[PDB]
Amino acid sequence: RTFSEEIKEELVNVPFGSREEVISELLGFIKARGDLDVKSRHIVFSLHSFAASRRLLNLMKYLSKPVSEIIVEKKKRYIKITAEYSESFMVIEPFFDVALFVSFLRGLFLSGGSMTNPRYHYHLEINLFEEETLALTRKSLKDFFNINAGIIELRNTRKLYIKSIKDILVFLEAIGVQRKLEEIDRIVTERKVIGDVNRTVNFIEANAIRTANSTARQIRAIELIKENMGLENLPEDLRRVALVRLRNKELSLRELGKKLNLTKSQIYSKLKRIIKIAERFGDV
Ligand code: NA
Image 1 (cartoon, rainbow, N blue to C red):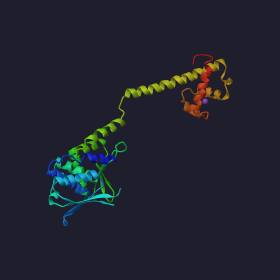
Image 2: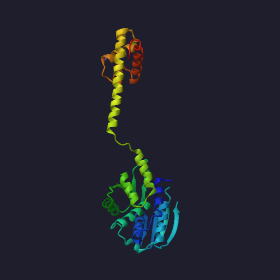
Image 3: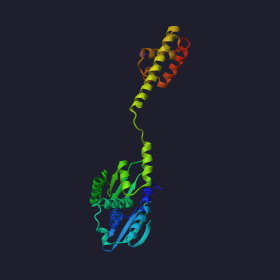
Image 4: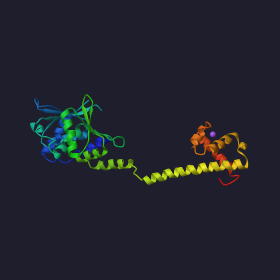
């Protein structure tokens, strides 16, 4: 089951605050996915969500309004719900009020909205044809909940989207999601790693101390060999490595390697051999 539909399942039995909030949520369904025909007295809803379809049926039941037909129009296939038109449906001003607006948002989201699995993306969207509706919705999201949302063009439709995981949680909780807010936080909190600047400094020092102690140990090993047997009496490939280290004592192993067409690991293996040889003569 998609993460999005799991969120929508939580909303199927959210309370019906009042008749006004019920009609406001229905208007959300109507605006997003309703093909309205006042003359023939019907509304055709096209829904890709079963959670959304069940919520729509529960709203119509609350209002005591009959739904006449439920069919699948033959992934791209969708649910067609035909219901009776009532002028009361269109009388509500859904933005005027945070209670009315939250119900409108729930309707918009259930019918035409979706949300990405936050393990992969931060994305919650609402698809809508009308341009005014989307702008007004975006303004009310900001005024009421301080939620910043962008807008996207798709020719067939336009998308309102929220990319802040903070704003997404506020949005979801506002419309009545509960269980899944905990799962989202466990995912968000688990991607995080916080702080210690002193731990960072400690780590950087430790690596620098390792590198310095190694380099000193290389130099010391080369000096002992030079004193006791002569570098000229090393195997040719170790001899060049000993000289390059001794002549370039502040270079990294990578940079020492470049001077002999050797990789860092190659020059490092040779330095280890040189140190092994120098144990003969003294502490290294
Ligand atoms: Na050199």
